[PDB]
Image 1 (cartoon, rainbow, N blue to C red):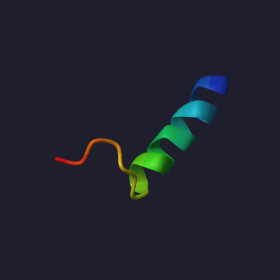
Image 2: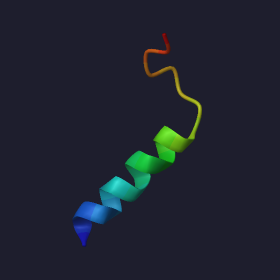
Image 3: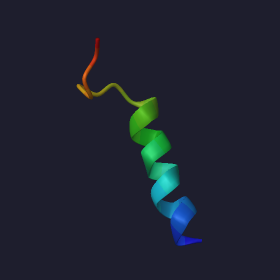
Image 4: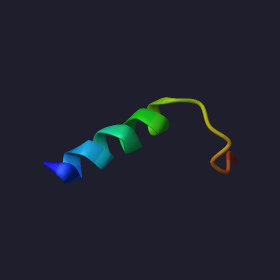
Length: 23
């Protein structure tokens, strides 16, 4: 369950406001 461990956080940053190329 290490996959979900990194996925859960991926989704968490995605849930957050980031300057991940906002067009």
